[PDB]
Amino acid sequence: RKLERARDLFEQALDGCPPKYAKTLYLLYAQLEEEWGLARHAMAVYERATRAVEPAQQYDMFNIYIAEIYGVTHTRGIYQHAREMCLRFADMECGEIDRARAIYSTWKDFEVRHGNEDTIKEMLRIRRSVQATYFMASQMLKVSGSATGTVAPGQSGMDDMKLLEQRLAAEAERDQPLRAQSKILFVRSDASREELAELAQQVNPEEI
Amino acid sequence: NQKEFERVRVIYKYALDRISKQELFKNYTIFEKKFGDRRGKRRFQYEEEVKANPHNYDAWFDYLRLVESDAEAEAVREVNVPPIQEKRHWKRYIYLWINYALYEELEAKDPERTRQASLELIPHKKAKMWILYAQFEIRQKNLSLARRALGTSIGKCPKKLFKVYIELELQLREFDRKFLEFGPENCTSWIELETILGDIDRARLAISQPRLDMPEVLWIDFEIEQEETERTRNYRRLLQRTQHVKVFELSSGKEGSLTKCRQKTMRNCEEKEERLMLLESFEEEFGTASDKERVDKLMEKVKKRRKVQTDDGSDAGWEEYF
């Protein structure tokens, strides 16, 4: 063991060597000592190689104690990309919104958060899109349809107008649907919507 | 870098006794570095850097500082245990919003208290029906979890919507381990709600009879439950309940005649249908009830052909009626 640790003290060059040595102590099941090695590696190689260490170090240390605060802190230190998402996915099921804030802290990432928020219940998801707006309009457009359909209800309908106006013939069918939905009141706005989509047909045809 | 252990701790402790008074972000960074030096049992500064940063999070407003009180208290809990609970109690109570801390603290407060039993329960519980609920399932349950572990929260929860239902199930479980606790639920059901306690007591003959009498005395869904129960037990009283309830309700009276008078269904049925049509183009239930009466008749081919004759007879009579 000490004969091996002499390597840890000196002649460092590549990580492979590091993971190998930690695997030695793991084979001897020193466990916590092994985690220390990953502490000593990462102080060296910075946000590049350190990730190559860190992904296995996380998967393993979470596998060990399974104590929350220590590993939680370890990801906290760690955080300074997908690794954050795996890790966060772990923490939520072993505060949730806090994690969603972390993922929030790209379209696919936006899609995920929204999914986990839906898992915490429906109400947040409509809320999520507003964050979402700031190809994204397609995701945004989908949210508006989902959101436009959903509705507070007056703010939601006016939001449907704000979204339909936010930015394509199917979308024209969407705005026309929003106009048609009114009990003889969504006509003017509907014809205005088809007019705007026609204007989009004009700007599209104008393109070379 | 000089492989010093004790001298580094001397430097670190000699530094962080005066230098944090400005404030302690570099203190937390050097704490993480000392946790790094200890890595390359020794996670003491892991707690000290987290707890200092938790308190370091500024309290602005009332709910923001009370939200932080939930964070650092959980951090203190997992890792003066009474004084941290007392400072947490003043932070939640000292809230500007003064509406959401009642639901936030109660949780935290209860947890702290739990972490002796008689004094903690009296503080949390601190009205006529609540004392009646306590005397039925306080000493009787004799249990760490449920009688005393829902003897306070349950009372607190109501003021739940399902309190008269949960209290009736609590007495039925406590009495059996019974007609004394079930009658207390049946008496509190009358004070729609009584039909729930009536259908439950009968499921455990006499209960069924009680379920009928009660319904009768009281007075579309409520009578459908009492009619289906008296019909399933083993067709006279099923028709009597239909006459004093159905007058969805028209469709229910047709479904009642199919089951009760299955083994003068065509005559009476058709008469009723026509009457309904006259008492308000709307003859889609006369051709549909006649087509089901023909198909339901015992005979396949002969049974299906008879259903076509019965269905077409209603359609021909319906199409020739203005």
Image: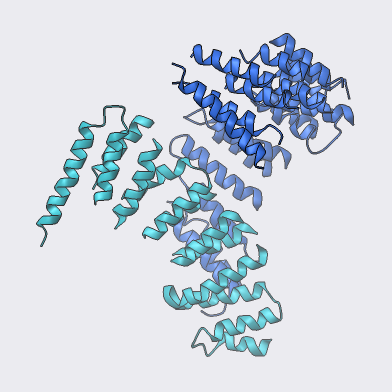
- Tell which chain the image draws in cyan: A
Q: Is residue B106 left or right of residue A114?
A: right
Spot occupied by residue B114 in the image (x, y as percentages of width and height): 73, 39
Q: Residue at x 60, y 50 (%)?
A: B75
Q: Camera-side residue: A166 or B221?
A: B221
Residue B207 shown left or right of residue B129 in the figure: right
Query: Viewer-proximal residue, B193 or B296?
Result: B296
Residue at 52% over, 38% down: B66
Please tell me which residue lies in front, B92 or B291: B291
- In this view of the protein, which residue sits in the foreground, A51 or B270? B270
Q: In which quadrant will I find the N terminus of chain A?
A: bottom right
Left or right of A189, for residue A152: right
Q: Is residue B139 left or right of residue A161?
A: right
Q: Which chain did the image draw in blue? A: B
In the picture, which quadrant includes the C terminus of chain A? bottom left
Which color scheme did the rendering employ for the protein?
A: by chain
Q: Position of residue A62 (x, y in %)?
A: 61, 65
Marks counted in the figure total 0
Q: Quadrant of residue B251?
A: top right
